[PDB]
Image (cartoon, rainbow over all chains, first blue to last red; front, side, top):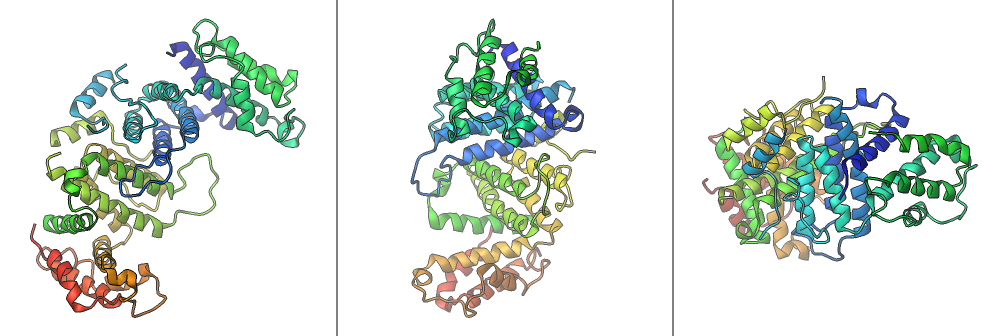
Length: 246
Length: 246
């Protein structure tokens, strides 16, 4: 599974995303903001599933949607992890467990909170109710980990996709992007599909490897940049940010 | 505020609503179902408010919507209270409070969880995050009470509206309603407006009075029935249900 420093790099990428919008975000934002947002996004995930026991059911859950909704929550989860280290524990979460206030489907501390496969409603409902509970006690680190475990249940390269997405945003941050100077070499192809083709160029193994993940991330980033028309000079700040230690 | 037996009668009305759909609901449904539904409806309430700190804000929250969304949650809250007494405590909730896992807005055990006025975003967000937390520990009784306190902050006669709504559903349960035999004496007027005019015929005080609330409820029910074309014979089962002891 995911080594601590991959997690730290992921949070560092999120820091950069937040900083572009608000360089002082760590001073303005609070741990309750992230907890709220994970709650609201978790609610929207659960809502893709036919949870209403009183509604007749036409079609099954759209798992493509569940995958991106997991990704949407990861941003807020990473943000809360960083916020939580700006000084906003384990004897608590076990006592919350023995009080019985994490749920389970009907008839590492994390793995009794996560229920698979996510393709089945009761298991997704319990899992994401538990993410909401986790948020509520500021355990952003367990949420982040649970989301990755969840992506893995859905054969979804979350880390890869997150990196691709990180780098599309660096392109969209520049004025050249809105001005139409930087264009897709392959016109018409949607964004989600160019990104997926960019994430395809490396393995899941490659983006999690404790030794050399940074190589694989840079290969994803280089792909996105190539596909979306970012010239060489404008890529350096994103590459340097990528390569920072944590 | 609201006496215990008004609360019990309200839950008894909900029992009847649930029974029409599923007479065996107390055996099939579980405490986690109600907790989930209160969570999902609370999330939709919060979503009427401009909580996204990163979105620019056009228009203020539509409080008419907040009022009905409080009512929507009350159904699930009452249902969970009943379910919780079908055998699915206070030394826990205080320890949850001292662990710090109910929230508050930035810079009776219930009243430090509820924040007013609900017209202001931070106060509504904290309040309804706390309802979600309450749900999560099966404190359906405190949720019910909090919802009433919340209706009171919004000058909303929740009990009145709930009763009106209870009785419109008794009419809609009959085949005559779908067959078009029972019609509004005042054609065209929307449902929500005929109900409000029905709730207007009694005071808030009247529907909470420990001594004589049942009189006032029956006056609301009689109004709704009159307005919606229910003939006398078909009203007896709803009146008898209304009048049951708890």
